[PDB]
Image (cartoon, rainbow over all chains, first blue to last red):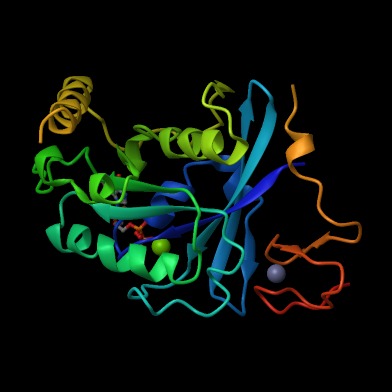
Length: 201
Length: 38
Ligand SMILES: Nc1nc2c(ncn2[C@@H]2O[C@H](COP(=O)(O)OP(=O)(O)O)[C@@H](O)[C@H]2O)c(=O)[nH]1
Ligand SMILES: [Mg+2]
Ligand SMILES: [Zn+2]
């Protein structure tokens, strides 16, 4: 079975635990690592070429960048950097998390995720989200509490790790039902805003 | 159709049962979490 260690990093309170826990089987089969203060969630996705397992490392704590225990980053094969679109400080720390990550994990695929986009009073909008462009990374809006775009980071990483740009997920994993509403018109506007930001200098 | 031919580590490679990290055949404990190889 093909499995990949995915480190999920970002400021405390950005929604990392809420996000990973959406995957019900990854939550029921999670593994606690006492020496590193981490819960490892085994997240299976079913692709058109079979199952892929992301073993997602979610810190139990509220660590600053640079403050995770030695071992957390070892043998990571991919990563998600998360910030909170309602908190500008957490986006301004994205470069610090990226620096912390590549210090130990030299050349791994990384997705940048801006969480809590269900909250209407959004502070970090598409026009301000540029770090992924400067570092040639992929970015997605997500809402952990509504499952909005849950599969997007994993599909992007799966394609990079398997070397197959046409890889697809044949079905969504069983997810905890949405706890908040993600307005479909808001999602469409945000997706449009990101496309416009990308197509201009 | 599968992607098995991309992942063929050395004989004796083993997975940590505590943190699921893949370890090398000569390792006697996990390189990430220090759990002993069973
Ligand atoms: N409205 C909304 N709240 C969220 C979302 N994700 C997390 N929250 C909340 O943000 C707080 C911190 O979430 P948590 O998962 O503990 O963040 P962590 O410290 O990065 O693990 C919690 O009160 C969550 O309920 C989201 O997508 N939308
Ligand atoms: Mg947490
Ligand atoms: Zn281990």
